[PDB]
Amino acid sequence: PAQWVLDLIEASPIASVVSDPRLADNPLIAINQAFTDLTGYSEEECVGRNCRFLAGSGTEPWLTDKIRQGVREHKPVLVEILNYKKDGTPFRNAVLVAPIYDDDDELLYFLGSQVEVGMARRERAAEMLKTLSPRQLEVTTLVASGLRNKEVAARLGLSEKTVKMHRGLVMEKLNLKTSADLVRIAVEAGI
Ligand SMILES: Cc1cc2nc3c(=O)[nH]c(=O)nc-3n(C[C@H](O)[C@H](O)[C@H](O)COP(=O)(O)O)c2cc1C
Picture 1 (cartoon, rainbow, N blue to C red):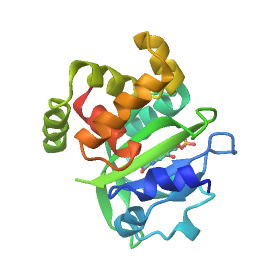
Picture 2 (tube, rainbow, N blue to C red; picture 1 turned 180 degrees about the vertical axis):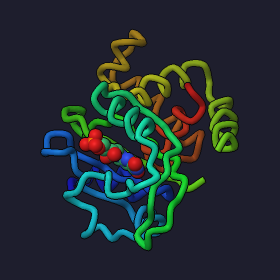
Picture 3 (cartoon, rainbow, N blue to C red; picture 1 turned 45 degrees about the vertical axis):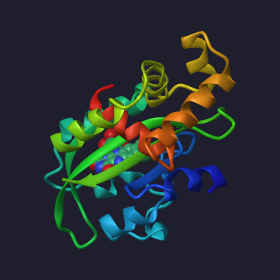
Picture 4 (cartoon, rainbow, N blue to C red; picture 1 turned 30 degrees about the horizontal axis):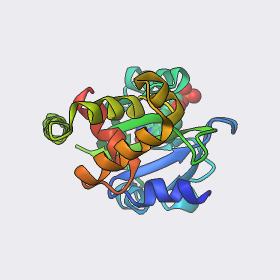
């Protein structure tokens, strides 16, 4: 588990995981404490496994199916799917799954975040984004969609350092500690 992997998720209070698509079946390579407190699954019993172990009998296949669609298109997707905790108790999981890049902006990975639940988080995220300047929104929209800093820059007619500066600016504006969290807020708002 690279340092950045754990920097990215362990800093988030929301149940979060990271998978590696260059491993067969795109298994998880890390989870944070909140995931364990949500599901009851310890990391030893998650890492190396595809996150489908949260799926069960009532899991609506059409929702599972847009997740796999978002994974293969490399696009963020957010659904409220029926999952099952460790004790077997079913729960409504507002699950985000989004393409994310490592520290070197080289390799693609997948970030998942899970919250037990709705439109309230949506309205919330919308209020947070409303405090950002027009340019910070541009940057936020583009990062959330998966792109690299290099790529976001290319789309705004910017340098990679300027974008970095802007991100740091939104991270402190929104009082966030990890990018995982910013991603989820953008997708929640539809931005
Ligand atoms: C990072 C990540 C997190 C995921 N989290 C969940 C989840 O919390 N709940 C869920 O039902 N599926 C989640 N998925 C997708 C499941 O693995 C999905 O059921 C599986 O990819 C489809 O299995 P199949 O198409 O081989 O039948 C996640 C996928 C990724 C990449």
